[PDB]
Length: 274
Image (tube, rainbow, N blue to C red; front, top):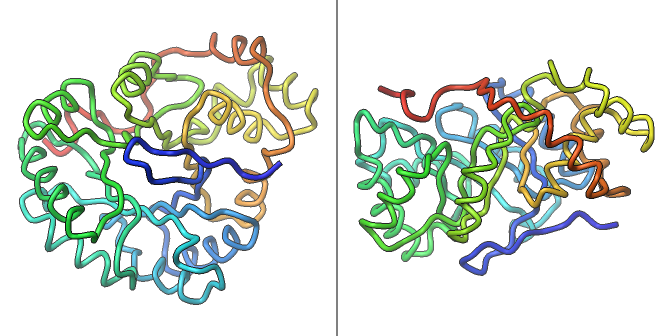
């Protein structure tokens, strides 16, 4: 089978599986992306706060894949909410791109409460064609309503922490109802601790001849989620992409559903930045 794509509410199309690039050094970043593009990834996710957009930009030039075939995502950092134009141009410059495929607000930072300002600015940069699609990361239902109520413009993506231990059934449901595509970061529950070692996952891994990480990524896919596993290890970047030759059954998905503990492993959307 071919890697699937998802059509966003604004009509733009996005690969359902992409590579997340975080903290890492330029060395790790350039090598990771070269490996991912080589194996088939067409979606690369980075952030201005990680300080490696330049490395990401250099890897894209070096690559043979054409720009138009690449779906690049970057994000607006917390202390730039009042100046999205300045932040975006700085990103586009470092990435060596004329436009970004998806621009996401990294965090709402409700304590500062400038996320509405950021969104209005993003709405304007999108009109000028510098951004194809706009969305957010780590936005809770009330943050989303506030954006909708104040601008009439709904995000096409809400990138949130979601894995077998915190399935976010509620936010996922709410996103979908409002035509917002849910995207998972930390899809492997940072390491797999409390997941890969579960009987349901292990048996699935053995039935399909896949690694537990491959089972979990397939789970995100069959759940209709866009997923961004993060990795800078060549063999794992490849492993995580080898999930197109099988699908989990309704019953198998139901079995994984029992793992939900509502356990958040990363920063708290309602407190981070405050």
